[PDB]
Amino acid sequence: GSSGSSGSPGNRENKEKKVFISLVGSRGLGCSISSGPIQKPGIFISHVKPGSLSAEVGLEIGDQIVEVNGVDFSNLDHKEAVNVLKSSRSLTISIVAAAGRELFMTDRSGPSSG
């Protein structure tokens, strides 16, 4: 085997990241999603399991789901966002890299069993 590619670079972005979650093989999502208020409605991650479909991508608490597989998760629900999330295996989630991290960061209570 012998083949090298330098590829053509050219990119400049930070916010709004695309994370594709694949529900195949030995790997199942293990992150919790929450529902924002009326002022900040949406789908935000609450927790991420170690070695989950979200952990693999490096998803963290705050990553608000604004889009999923080209879906409008900016006004979805915990049922619609889940149904759509459970709709197919492979889905392209578009987070804003800890969009609403303050929705959780703000004070650290630390629940036991929701």
Image: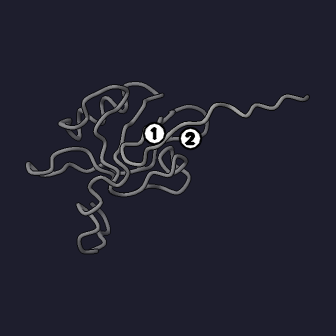
Q: Considering the image in quadrants, where does the C terminus appear?
A: bottom left
Identify the mark at residue 76; answer none if there is no mark.
none
As drawn, which residue projects farthest toward the left? 38
The span from disc 2 to disc 1 (Cα, nearest Å) is 15 Å
Compare marks 2 and 1 and give the one earlier in the sequence. 1
Residue at point 37%, 31% (across, down): 86
Q: Is residue 83 left or right of residue 58?
A: left
Residue 67 spot, x, y in % from top left: 31, 34
Residue 85 spot, x, y in % from top left: 36, 33
Q: Considering the image in quadrants, where does the N terminus appear?
A: top right
Of residues 90 and 64, the one drawn nearer to the viewer in this rendering: 64
Residue 100 spot, x, y in % from top left: 26, 55
Q: Which amino acid does label 1 sit on?
A: Val
Picture colour scheme: one colour
As drawn, which residue projects farthest toward the right? 1
Residue at point 35%, 51% (across, down): 63
Q: Is residue 51 left or right of residue 80?
A: right
Of residues 72 and 10, the one drawn nearer to the viewer in this rendering: 10
Foreground disc of the pair 2, 1: 1
Q: What element carries label 1?
A: strand
| Number of other residues with Cα within 10 Å of mark 2, as a class: few under 14, some 14 to 19, many 20 or more | some
Q: Is residue 63 left or right of residue 30?
A: left
Residue 88 spot, x, y in % from top left: 42, 25
Residue at point 48%, 28% (across, down): 90
Q: Cβ–Cβ below 8 Å for labels 2 and 1? A: no
| Number of other residues with Cα within 10 Å of mark 1, as a class: few under 14, some 14 to 19, many 20 or more | many
Q: Which amino acid does label 2 sit on?
A: Arg
Q: Name the residue under label 2.
A: 27
Q: Is mark 2 on a helix, strand or loop?
A: loop
Q: Mark 1 points at which residue?
A: 19
Residue at point 37%, 38% (across, down): 94
